[PDB]
Each structure stands twice: as C-alpha cells, then as structure tokens.
C-alpha cells in the first residue's frame, strides 16, 4: 500500500520530537504531495527548517500556510519567531503581534507563550537598537 | 512548549 497524508504528518511529528529534523521535513513533504491543501503540513515543516537554521526555507513554508489560512495564529507565530532569529526585529514583532490579537479574537487557550516571545523580541530589539 | 505548537491544528 502507501501511507495516507495524515499518517505521514504523524510520522513527521514523531521524527521532530525524535530530533531528526531532515527526516521530519521529508515526511511533511510527502504529506504535502498527497494533499497540498493542509496548512499544518507547511507550518510543521517550517518549524523543522527553523531548527535546522534554514531560515529562508522556513519563511517560505510559513507564507504557504498563510495563503491557506490567513488567520492562522500558529503560522504567524512561527513566522514571527523565524524573523526574530534573522535580526529582522521590526517584522518579527509585527507578526508576533498579529498572532496575539488573532489568538484573542479566536479565544484560544494557548497561554503566555506568544506574549513571552513578543516581549523577548521587543527587548532584544533595544539591544541592537 | 514546542510539542504543543507542533500538535496544534486549529
Ligand atoms: C505551554 C503550551 O502548552 N503552549 C501552547 C502552544 C500552542 C497551543 N496550540 C493549540 O493547542 C492549537 C496550545 C498550547
């Protein structure tokens, strides 16, 4: 037979926790081939690219998810995070901010985990001001 | 909490 896109995402999720980020990204890629219209495949592969320090690759997958779901709190948060590492402070804090009001409007039980990144991003900016 | 974000599909 051949695994479903859901099973490929699940296998990729396991390799991510397993710290095999190249392998996890490849599983997400095969999921995408089976069904290219599921946003979480892209955000999760982008997260792989952040860990591997391939920041352009992670930007692209975050942008692809935002085309599928412009309201994605997760895609904005990963996009904001990625831009923070590239010293693109002004972009990171804008995207991190939009994840915050989007999480507000959707009433999501995430926690102080977006404000934390937002504070650290804004005050890492004032260093290299 | 990178696991929580990873599993988040909403
Ligand atoms: C600490 C923690 O649990 N954070 C967290 C991040 C993301 C989400 N997202 C979804 O559940 C969709 C929940 C909790």
Image (tube, coloured by chain):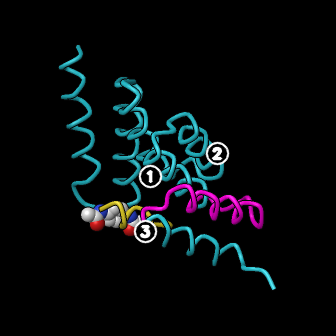
Q: Is residue A78 visible?
A: yes
A84 above or below A15? above
Asked which secondary structure carries label 3, the reply is: loop
Q: Which chain is cyan?
A: A
Magenta segment boundaries in residue numbering: A18-40
Chain under label 1?
Answer: A
Q: Which residue is mark 2?
A: A64
Q: Is mark 1 within 8 Å of ligand 1?
A: yes
Q: Is mark 2 within 8 Å of ligand 1?
A: no
Is A118 left or right of A43, judged from the image as shown? left
In terms of depth relative to the viewer, which is nearer, A37 or A84?
A84
State the quadrant of the C terminus of chain A: top left
State how far apart marks 1 and 3 are (Cα): 25 Å
Q: Which residue is mark 1?
A: A73
Q: Which chain is yellow?
A: B
Please give the count of numbered marks on the rendered protein: 3
| Residue drawn at (81%, 86%) of the image | A1
């Amino acid at each position: 037979k051949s695994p479903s896109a859901q099973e490929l995402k699940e296998q990729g999720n396991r390799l991510f926790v397993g710290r095999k980020y190249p392998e996890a990204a490849a599983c997400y890629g095969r999921a995408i081939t089976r069904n290219p219209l599921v946003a979480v495949y892209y955000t999760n592969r982008a997260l792989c690219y952040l860990k591997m320090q391939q920041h352009e690759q992670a930007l692209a997958d975050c942008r692809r998810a935002l085309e599928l779901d412009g309201q994605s709190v997760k895609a904005h948060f990963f996009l904001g995070q990625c831009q923070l590492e590239m010293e693109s402070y002004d972009e990171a804090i804008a995207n991190l901010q939009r994840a915050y009001s989007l999480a507000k409007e959707q009433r999501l039980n995430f926690g102080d985990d977006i404000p934390s990144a937002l504070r650290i991003a804004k005050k890492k900016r004032w260093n290299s001001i | 909490c990178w696991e929580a974000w990873l599993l988040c599909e909403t």
